[PDB]
Structure formats: C-alpha cells, structure tokens
Image (cartoon, rainbow over all chains, first blue to last red; front, side, top):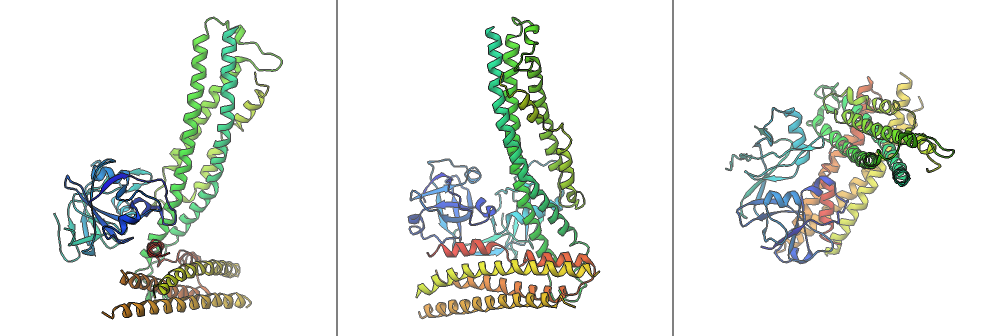
Length: 177
Length: 198
Length: 150
C-alpha cells in the first residue's frame, strides 16, 4: 500500500540481466516495514484492479516508502510516477504450472512455434504468471507481447488473494495457442 | 566570395566529424570479431549434440534428462553473445545516422548557394586543396559507403536462427568478406587528400 | 549463532569460486587429452592422473559444502526448540545441484579417457564446461540469500 516511482539507474550486474528484467526496487524500511522477504516473490495491485507478481529487491540508496517500478512493468500495470500501489508479501503456496494458454501479440501469420516456445521458456524461467496478464520475449532482438488466457496447475487448479496458490514456469510446462 | 567561404567552412567543418566517426566505426567493428568467432564455436558444439541419441551409450544411460538440460544451457550462453552483437550493431546504426545527417547538411548549404557561384569557381583546384567539386563528390561517396556497409551487415546478421546450424557456422567468413569488398579504406584516403584542410 | 550463518554464506561464495577455478584448469586438461588422443587417431597417463587429482580437489570442495549443509540443518533444528528455513532450503538446493554436477564430471572423465568418434568428444568437452546442472538461479539465489546478511 505505497506509492510508485520510476526505475532506478544503479544496475548491479552481480545477477544475470535476464533477472534484471523482472524486478522491483525498494528501500530498507520498505523491506522491514511491510515484512517483505528478499528474493521472494511479491504481489502488486493497482486500484484499477490489476494484480501482478514480481521479485522484490532492495537497492542500496532509495527513498523509503516507494516502489521503483520498471517501465514495461509500469505500462503492464498502467500507473505513472507519483501514483500509489498496493504491495503484498506473497505468503501462499507456489507450484510448477503444467500447461499454459497463449495469445499472440500481432496475430500475424506465425513464426516457428517450436523455437518460439523454446525462446519463451528459456527467457521466462522462474516467473509466476496469472491469467489475463502478458509476456515479453525477445525473439532475436524484436519483441512480442504474449497474453495468457488460462492456466492449468499441476493439480488441475485451473484459473480464469494474497493467501492462495500461484504458479511459475519451467521447461516441463507446455503451451497451447 | 563569401559563398565560397561558406561552403569552405561547411566542408572543413564536416570533415573532422567524419574522421572521429570513422574511428568509432572502426573500434566498434573490431569488437565484433572475437564475439563472432565464439558464436561460431557454440554453433559447432550445438551441432555436435544432435548427432547422438543419449538413450543408447553406456555411461550416460544412467543419466536421464540430460540432452535437454544441456541444450537449454548452450542456447543461453549463445543468446547472451548474440545480444552483445546486437549492441555493437546499434553503435553502427548511430554512426550512419550521424554521418548522413551531416553530409546532407553540407549539400543543402551548397544547393542554397550554387547559383551565384560559377561552377568554374567551384571547379578549380589550388596548390594546397583539391577541387570543391571533388570534395562534395567524396562526401557523397562516404555517405553511400557507410549506408551500404551498415545495411549489408544487418541483413547478414539478422538471418541467424538456431535451427540452421550449418549457416550459423559460416558467419566468421561471410562477415570478413562483407568487410573486404568495399574500396580499400575510403575515409582514410579522403582524409589524407583533404589533410591540408581547405 | 547467526554468525555461523554469515560464515556459511561467505564460505558458499568462496567455495563456488574455487570450484569454477578448478573446473577451468580441468577443462584445459581434458582439452589436452582430447587433442593428444585424436593425434593418435602410453604417456598420456600422467595427464589422466592429474585430471583425477583435479576431481579429488573437487571432491574435497564437495565434502566441505556437505559439512556446511549439515551445520545449517543443525542450526535449523536448534531454532526448532519451540526467516531461517529459507537458509536451509537454499543450501539444500545448492548441495543437490553441485553433487549431481560432480557425478556428471566423474562420468565424463571415465568415458573421456578413451572415446570413439569425435562427436562424442566435443559433446563431452561441452558437458564438462557448461556444467549443465546449475540453473544459474544459484548466483541470484546466493546473492539473494547473501544480501539477507552482510
């Protein structure tokens, strides 16, 4: 339940850039205030009704009480600097989602769906999806925007809440269009 | 008179840009060589991991779920390289846009003045400077050279698909060729011929 | 008490580093073996032996990591007198990863000494270098746990 600012310019290349993509940047009091667990997924909610998970991280030097959000993230949620947000330390259960529905960005003819799926997996590892949200791959430099229609958990826990079940992606997960 | 001084200032104002930008082009190009070599190498490895089956070989047999867990590593270690190449090519693109803008500026000034300056005054060489006409010609030739080089580079580099593991293993040669086919060091000789600034 | 946890963290760091260094040297060795073999289409034995020595250094690394894991589990149990489990599962993921990795390295040495067609040889050299049993989340993971302490 805090406010949003733009992403910072203090990238710490001790982790791979792939994870530098999926992140949010906070402060120390932010961590020790709403009881946030470093490196453990965290939920964000917009007053409009958007819910999206990410991987929290406290960056050395930051104005407390704010969430430094990514540009692509700021669009995917649709809030600008100065806006407020509702953050929640994700406490429920997680699972390896079995199979997931896909919606193509442009709905053009196609590209090689096998290699496409490969690229999606190898670049979206360790990310928790939720239906109606979207993805961001880089198929040889050019980006797409894949939308998720439905989700099937390993235990048939299909979807269309901070204490609930959520599902990440892994090589075993398969995709449907 | 003053128009001639105008185009003269324009010219020996545009050239140093061309020099420095050529240096940047060059350095940025030199980084690409070892990267591309390593990428050919990763291609070769990944090539020699489909010629097996991994279900029938004595030792590895006790290792289920390996062939995948390997590929899905080689591909990452390749993809990072290829994004580095992408960065280099972005540098290249910056330099072509810079040079093209400047050259067009020069021509536009000239066209602005080329009615009150008899082309004979344009076209006469001095003891310490080539003919104005030849200067504009060389500028235009530099711009066209940069454009063609950049665009041929890109339509070579963006035809890489994990899946044609033969083609991806010939890059380091097709690239070098694309370099060894322009005229030998244009910017170098132009820079010399104009060294005596005017 | 938690000082032991911080020591576990820093030891994880330095241990992984030493691992990587040894793997580099060993990769050099295996490259030499592959080339020397393929040149022959009774002295490479010294090479094979020092490669085995590399494996033994690896094994020492492994046993130190195992001790660290056990100590962490013990501190977990002690705090179970009446986040920290975080640390246990972290170290357990790390341990299982690196242990399977070690097994794969052992098998690649075994098979590598005398191989047939070259394609096996390239695939093996690869399987050594890329160590395909570390999801690299480890680095993140380690950092993610490391920054929970100093």
